[PDB]
Amino acid sequence: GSSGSSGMTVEQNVLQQSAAQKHQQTFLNQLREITGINDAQILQQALKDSNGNLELAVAFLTAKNAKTPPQEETSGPSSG
């Protein structure tokens, strides 16, 4: 079981590393915010291509759905 062993230690995190990296769900969710995409058919597609590389999943996504250039048209900018 779990039990009340150990008192606040950093011995139950170092594991997360990698172990987490290997999690499709975690990936999609990752590319979900990164690119902000929601569709899974798009998130997965990126992953599939990347072959398991977020950077590639983002690059592929980024090199597909980006903001339009400073052309003559409406849009509506934003700032703080």
Image (cartoon, helix red, strand yellow):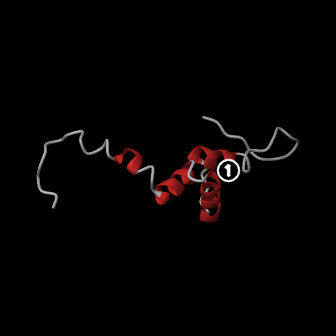
Relative to 72, is 5 on the left or the right?
left
Residue 11 sits above or below residue 2 on the image: above
Q: Residues within 10 Å of mark 1 (few under 14, many from 20)?
A: many
Looking at the image, the residue that sits furthest to the front is: 51
Q: Residue at x 60, y 53 (%)?
A: 51
Q: What percent of the width, then of the height, locates residue 48?
A: 61, 58
Which quadrant holds the N terminus?
Answer: bottom left
Q: Please, what is the three-letter code of the amino acid marked with disc 1?
A: Leu
Q: Secondary structure at mark 1?
A: helix
Looking at the image, the residue that sits furthest to the right is: 72
Relative to 65, is 40 on the left or the right?
left
Q: Residue at x 13, y 42 (%)?
A: 7
Closer-to-camera residue (45/39): 45
Looking at the image, the residue that sits furthest to the left is: 4
Q: What percent of the width, then of the height, locates residue 8?
A: 18, 41
Q: Residue at x 53, y 57 (%)?
A: 28
Residue 37 sits above or below residue 74 on the image: below
Closer-to-camera residue (29/21): 21
Task: Quickly name the residue at label 1.
Answer: 61
Q: Count how many numbered circles sit on residues in the image.
A: 1
Residue 31 sits above or below residue 7 on the image: below
Q: Quadrant of residue 14?
A: top left
